[PDB]
């Protein structure tokens, strides 16, 4: 074989000091970060060739980086284009990458990784091929193997080496299955790195110092990984060990429990590669890993997840939906109206980002409970070692609870989070409109009420705008920004920049009842209720939701959404249609909503819905549900139930695009994933159409054929919009 | 068209798992002891006419590895032409060996065959051999592997079998097995296990608990040992059986089969083979059938296997006098009875594995022999024997008293 | 009286033991790949008519434990009613599965059965399952256990086969296998092994050494690895064969079978089953026979098994066109040829396990399929397939081209 791809700029600087230690400093001149592209493979191939050729004069190797980060990921642009006919080329490429690292790993001399910044994916895999890892304990540095988040797996030896280091169970659960990212101190605890230094200037000196000490203290074992020694024992045992074999059958079942049966192939591939690799020698394990990697890259799910979680996320974070030309504006003091769970979480993420927050409610005790929401989160973070006492005190000190409107003096950014009622929001805003700063943002956490109508309650409608968060705010990353008819671009840019500042992902929506997320998620829950009214078993409906990939089944979600709210939405939808001169046709779900309301089972808040509730806990489906709707009389295939929910949201997403509610498919995909809970394996409700894979085929045309099949069997609402036809 | 007949069917007593009498006995010795008993019953039998020895064994490793059937032929002094083959179709291995022996007789290419099984679960625990369906993640994930006890609980949940229903069947199993032992039904076919000095090791099914009460069974906890105690398996089962909200865990150590040691042997031959050797046929193998059902619920194979063997023999349920279904779990028996509308008085009339134990590779040959004796004792005509099998398989056999 | 016919017979290439191409392939995958090929050849085959899948496997542990045949049925998407059973009759397991399938077809209780074997010796080494004949001292002592290579050397000593005689046969095996491969004889039945991406893993029998010379074979050392290198085994063999003074150790790695990985599959059914499915019969199973000889010399079972199957079919040696005997050791083939006076040109005409390897549980089904192809290629009538078996057993099968 060869260290080269076949038989490109230079990205690696070579330096051999008088003591014989070679420093390989990675510095790709074409980008701001070192990536596993064609130039790296060629540069590393030449460097490894030179290490072998000069092996008599080389005593150690230090792998360092000249960039802000160590090494970040591979080349997604190339991987996303890999077709099934390209599986051989993909296999050969990762085999070549790992041949380079395996040679580096078996040089007979110690190799140290000097990790100065982030080392993610292929970057960590490089450091794992070394015998010792030193990391600079600097902020913003992250270590991990997040390949699974793109539908891939660590195909540069990450699976094989972490399993050799930690065993099957620990490597899978803690490193590989969720692509967990680790801070340098967190990475040293689990053994991902071996020692830390305070500054990046100490790294390469500490790497050479460790090499010098290693040659003196451990001459026979210098440069030999634990799994390359005679008598190596895998932590936790091999699959043949009786201890591991007793629990090994529960690893795929625990996986199915966490994934809920969703069709996401990457975690299954990682576990298979991990266990199959633990049964054979290292070099055989590595080649098995390459075959599973090739299986994922050429598959459709990886193409969905690369498009959504790499390209679409990048285009959004680059400001694709931000008004062009407008500059930045600092936020001096944020004011939150309403100390409920939404406003309390909004105050938390704002203060955590460094902003001063005034948290106002109609009761000082209520406003204090709101700040207590942040207190409990910080106590949890302090107990897990995820923050310091000094940093935590500064966060909470930035939250000032109050019940007096006069305390909103100096606020230049208002975020209202009260009950979804127009007359209420009008009086709430009118109380502080003259107290806050003149050019203050007047933001409203509204789920469906059009922003244009809410803006009339304030004088400066140009500064009124929808800022829609998602519960729990501290863990949900989407902010849905809705422009009213009179919302200015300057206001949109200021909220856009605020969203990035608090670490969230913005999408920009034009004013329309239901906006994007509430409207689309409504078609999801309404489709489930229609199945319940048709006589489908409630348990099958919940399974169809979880196996489709949604984070919560739809009947459970309906109880949380409150059926009274769903009834008011249907009333407002009907009013809007017939006020425009049209004829309203009710969704089949509305009769189900009305029946449950009539029975007094209107959701979790009332204490009874599709589920029963006791001690603040959900305690199974209501047994009277089956008699109320004749459950079991309709038994459609589970895949039809899954497709009904997925297609309903995908069709509704396309309508939002056709109407101008959304301006980019990137916003449609990320908005659906992060806000609507659309299954990540689809890449988003718009990517679902172009990426659809079913019995009818693949692509948009197959999506349309399956949509027409669902239409003939379940109703004309599944007929595709005109924009999807030839 | 060469009919296969059963000439002898014997078994050892079943020794318990904890402080069991058979734990000191090599599983090879269990088989050789039954061979010695057959030789003791027919000393002038020309053993050169025996062409094969077919033993079921579910964990063929260690003491049970390396083709234990051939080891038994050589250790017992049987002729070197007598073959020896081990097979594994999980819990049905003992009956599969009998069926395979009968089919070899029908082919005309074998005239006289020994069939049976052996399983020393106290020495070779269940799962000692491994396997991809459980231990290979890609195979486990795709097949949706679920431990058998959870399939048994899912059956009880789907069919509405309560905890008192399965505990009522377990009580009947203890009572029927005690009445069979005290009545002498087992005296002729249970061969006491002795040491090399002729000293008694075990002469009875020591797993039985004849003093079991309905109150005592109610106090037992649901199964919380082995793979069932691990996580995720309930979720996997309900992902396939998506109309079931929650699994009712009704099975315990008191309404499930016991872990035991034991062996069984059956002599099968043609009419000309038996007439040449002065053997009297006890029963005729009418028909065999292999089928299966969903592998996730796993334990519903007996129903399609039974329907197939009845159609093959041109018979109905009413034509069968005795039904024998291995008592791996109480709900499996209640499900089988509900599926085919089997009267209670036809089903496992001498008790089953809940009382006496389930020595995996041997059980199928034990309950086959149990039905040969009970047909002769009642002077009844036909018996149907079947067992639930891992992976969702099913095997059923019809015998007719001769 | 229901004739059993062979409709398909295929196999994987055999991957070598050291740096082998198949070492990364799970043995379950080897079987599933052959199932996919059968489905690829008959896509409209109603798989619900397949009632069983019977796989021989000599070391059914780890990757090969837990009834791998049932795992293959479920992993390949075959119907849940298709059964699945593993058997072990040592090196003959693959042919035993075929014979058992044919006898199930003759019984009239099974209509369409898949039979074969699988053995990944690079992943599951020989002896991984243990066994009492070797590991139990009382059984080992009484049976006078001797490794097979010493029995092979004893045969050469008793029959006067010199080191040059066995090396001459090994050279012919390499040459015949090379001519068969280069002639395209194996193109239709050796199914290349591919990964989940369709990328080639192995498409040829990589254990072959077509450049073998008589001089190169003479330089090899007698077998000095494994149990044969241990002490006392020569003395044990000569205590039974007391008229032999000294054993001539003539067998080496170059005149013995190779350690390899591989699988094989055969589809067997009745005439009505094939006609219902549009299948064309390739051969008919005429007769099977199980016999055996002394277990100490171990490897002389093929002769009495062959005589028995010939008498059963009413045939003689002259009535057989092709003889196929597994090449576990060169002297075993020379002994079999000397016993029955077999012409060279009838014996292992396409080479054997010395060139291509001996994947224990699969070999019997591989060489069976090899004879189905060669009978059709030569337009010949009858073939006899047999293998030597540990413990002194023997199995032989006669097929007739249809």
Image (spheres, coloured by chain):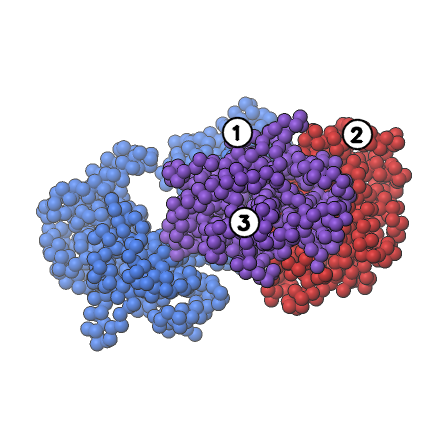
Chain colours: A blue, B purple, C red
| Residue that mark 3 sits on | B324
Viewer-closest of C219 and A477: C219
> What residue is drawn where x is 72% and y is 61%?
C1
Q: Position of residue A113 (x, y in %)?
A: 49, 36
Dot 2 surroundings within 10 Å: few (below 14), some, or many (20 or more)? some
Q: Chain of mark 3?
A: B
Q: Chain of mark 2?
A: C
- The answer to whether the residues at label 2 and label 1 have Cβ atoms under 8 Å apart is no
> What residue is drawn where x is 17% and y is 64%?
A453
> What residue is drawn where x is 60% and y is 61%?
B312
Q: Which mark is residue C259?
A: none
**Residue lying at the far top of the rendered structure:** A217
The mark lying in front, picked from 3 and 2, is 3
- Count the labels in the image: 3
Whether callout 3 and callout 2 share a subunit is answered no
Q: Chain of mark 1?
A: B
Q: Position of residue A231 (x, y in %)?
A: 59, 30
Q: Position of residue B220 (x, y in %)?
A: 40, 37
Q: Position of residue A630 (x, y in %)?
A: 32, 63
Is residue B110 visible in the rendered structure shown here?
A: no
> What residue is drawn where x is 66% and y is 35%?
B33
The mark lying in front, picked from 2 and 1, is 1
Viewer-closest of A81 and C21: C21
Label 2: state its secondary structure.
helix
Q: Which mark is residue C236?
A: 2
Q: Which mark is residue B19?
A: 1
């Amino acid at each position: 074989s060869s260290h080269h791809h076949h038989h490109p700029d230079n990205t690696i600087q070579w330096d051999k000091d008088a003591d014989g230690i070679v420093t390989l400093t990675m510095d790709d001149p074409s980008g701001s970060t070192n990536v596993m592209n064609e130039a790296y493979i060629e540069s590393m191939g030449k460097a490894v060739d030179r290490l072998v050729a000069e092996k008599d004069s080389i005593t150690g190797v230090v792998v360092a980086s000249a960039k802000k980060t160590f090494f970040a990921g591979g080349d997604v642009k190339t991987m996303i284009q890999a077709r099934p006919e390209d599986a051989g080329d993909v296999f050969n490429t990762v085999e070549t990458i790992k041949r380079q690292l395996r040679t580096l790993e078996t040089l007979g001399k110690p190799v140290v990784a000097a990790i100065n910044g982030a080392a993610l994916g292929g970057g960590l895999e490089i450091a794992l091929a070394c015998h010792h890892r030193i990391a600079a304990d600097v902020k913003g540095s992250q270590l991990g193997l997040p390949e699974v988040t793109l539908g891939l797996l660590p195909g540069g030896g990450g699976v094989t080496r972490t399993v050799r280091m930690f065993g099957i169970q620990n490597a899978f659960v803690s490193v590989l299955a969720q692509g967990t990212r680790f801070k340098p101190a967190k990475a040293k605890e689990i053994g991902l790195v071996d020692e830390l230094v305070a500054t990046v200037e100490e790294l390469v000196p500490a790497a050479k110092a460790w090499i010098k000490e290693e040659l003196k203290a451990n001459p026979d074992g210098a440069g030999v990984q634990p799994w390359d020694k005679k008598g190596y024992k895998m932590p936790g045992g091999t699959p043949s060990s009786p201890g591991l074999a007793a629990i090994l059958p529960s690893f795929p079942s625990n996986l199915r429990k966490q994934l809920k049966g969703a069709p996401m192939p990457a975690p299954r591939a990682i576990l298979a590669a991990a266990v199959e690799g633990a049964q054979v020698d290292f070099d055989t394990a590595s080649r098995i890993e390459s075959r599973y990697f090739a299986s994922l890259v050429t598959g459709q799910v990886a193409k969905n997840m690369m498009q959504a979680f790499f390209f679409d996320l990048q285009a959004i974070n680059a400001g694709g939906s931000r008004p062009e030309g407008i500059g930045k504006t600092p936020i001096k003091r944020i004011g939150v109206l309403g100390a409920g769970m939404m406003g309390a979480g909004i105050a938390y993420v704002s203060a955590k980002a460094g902003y001063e927050v005034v948290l106002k409610d109609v009761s000082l005790e209520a406003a204090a409970k709101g700040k207590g929401y942040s207190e409990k989160l910080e106590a949890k973070a302090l107990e897990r070692g995820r923050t310091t006492q000094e940093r935590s005190d500064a966060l909470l000190a930035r939250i000032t609870p109050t019940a007096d409107a006069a305390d909103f003096k100096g606020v230049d950014f208002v975020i209202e989070a009260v009950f979804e009622n127009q007359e209420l929001k009008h009086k709430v805003f009118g109380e502080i409109e003259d107290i806050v700063e003149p050019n203050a943002i007047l933001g409203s956490n509204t789920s469906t009420l059009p922003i244009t109508g809410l803006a009339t309650g304030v004088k400066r409608q140009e500064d009124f705008i929808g800022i829609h968060f998602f519960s729990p705010v501290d863990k949900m990353p989407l902010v849905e920004i809705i422009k009213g008819e009179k919302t200015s671009d300057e206001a949109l840019a200021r909220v856009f920049d605020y969203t990035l500042a608090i670490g969230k992902t913005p999408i920009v929506v034009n004013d329309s009842r239901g906006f994007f997320t509430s409207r689309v998620i409504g078609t999801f829950v309404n489709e489930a209720l229609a199945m319940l009214g048709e006589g489908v078993e409630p348990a099958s409906i919940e399974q169809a939701g979880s196996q489709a990939g949604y984070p919560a089944p739809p009947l459970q979600l309906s109880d949380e959404l409150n059926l009274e709210l769903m009834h008011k939405i249907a009333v407002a939808t009907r009013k809007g249609v017939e006020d425009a001169g049209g004829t309203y046709q009710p969704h089949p779900a509305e009769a189900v909503v009305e029946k449950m309301i009539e029975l007094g089972r209107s959701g979790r808040l009332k204490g009874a819905g599709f589920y029963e509730y006791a001690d603040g806990k959900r305690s199974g489906l209501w047994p009277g549900l089956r008699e109320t709707f004749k459950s079991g009389s309709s038994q459609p295939p589970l895949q039809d139930m899954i497709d009904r929910m997925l297609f309903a949201e995908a069709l509704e997403t396309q309508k939002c695009l056709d109407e101008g509610v959304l301006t980019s498919t990137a916003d449609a995909n990320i908005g659906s994933i992060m806000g609507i809970g659309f299954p990540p394996w689809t890449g988003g409700s718009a990517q679902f159409i172009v990426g659809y894979s079913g019995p009818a085929g693949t692509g948009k045309a197959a999506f349309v054929a399956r949509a027409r099949e669902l239409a003939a069997a379940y109703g004309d609402r599944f007929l595709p919009p005109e924009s999807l036809l030839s | 068209s060469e009919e296969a007949f059963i000439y002898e069917a014997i078994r050892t007593p079943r020794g318990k798992q904890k402080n069991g009498s058979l734990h000191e006995v090599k599983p090879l010795s269990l088989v050789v002891g039954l061979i010695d008993e057959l030789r003791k019953r027919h000393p002038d039998l020309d053993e050169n006419l025996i062409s094969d020895v077919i033993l079921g064994c579910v964990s063929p490793v260690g003491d049970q590895g390396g083709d234990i059937a051939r080891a038994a032929v050589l250790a017992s002094g049987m002729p070197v032409t007598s073959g020896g083959v081990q097979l594994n179709r999980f819990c049905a291995s003992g009956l599969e060996a009998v069926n395979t022996a009968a089919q070899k007789v029908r082919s005309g290419w074998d005239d006289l065959v020994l069939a049976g099984g052996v399983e020393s679960m106290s020495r070779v625990p269940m799962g000692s051999d491994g396997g991809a369906m459980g231990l290979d993640p890609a195979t486990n994930y795709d097949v949706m592997f679920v431990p058998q006890s959870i399939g048994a609980d899912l059956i009880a949940t789907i069919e509405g079998f309560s905890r008192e229903d399965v505990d009522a069947y377990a009580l009947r199993s203890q009572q029927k097995a005690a009445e069979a032992w005290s009545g002498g039904y087992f005296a002729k076919s249970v061969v006491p296990v002795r040491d090399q000095n002729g000293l008694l090791i075990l002469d009875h099914d020591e797993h039985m608990r004849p003093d079991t009460t309905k109150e005592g069974l109610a106090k037992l906890k649901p199964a919380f040992e082995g793979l069932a105690a691990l996580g995720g398996f309930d979720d996997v089962a309900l992902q396939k059986y998506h109309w079931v909200e929650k699994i009712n865990h009704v099975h315990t150590g008191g309404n499930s089969s016991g872990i035991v040691d034991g062996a069984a042997l059956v002599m099968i031959g043609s009419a000309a083979a038996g007439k040449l050797q002065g053997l009297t046929p006890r029963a005729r193998i009418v028909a065999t059938a292999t089928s299966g059902a969903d592998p996730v619920i796993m334990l519903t194979g007996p129903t399609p296997a039974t329907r197939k063997v009845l159609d093959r023999a041109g018979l109905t349920v009413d034509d069968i006098d005795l039904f024998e279904l291995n008592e791996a779990f109480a709900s499996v028996v209640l499900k089988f009875q509900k599926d085919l509308n089997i009267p209670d008085e036809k089903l496992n009339v001498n008790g089953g594995a809940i009382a006496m134990g389930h020595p995996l590779g041997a059980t199928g040959a034990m309950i086959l022999g149990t039905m040969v004796d009970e047909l002769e004792r009642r002077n009844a005509r036909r018996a149907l024997i079947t067992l639930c099998i891992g992976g969702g398989m099913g095997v059923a056999t019809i015998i007719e008293r001769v």
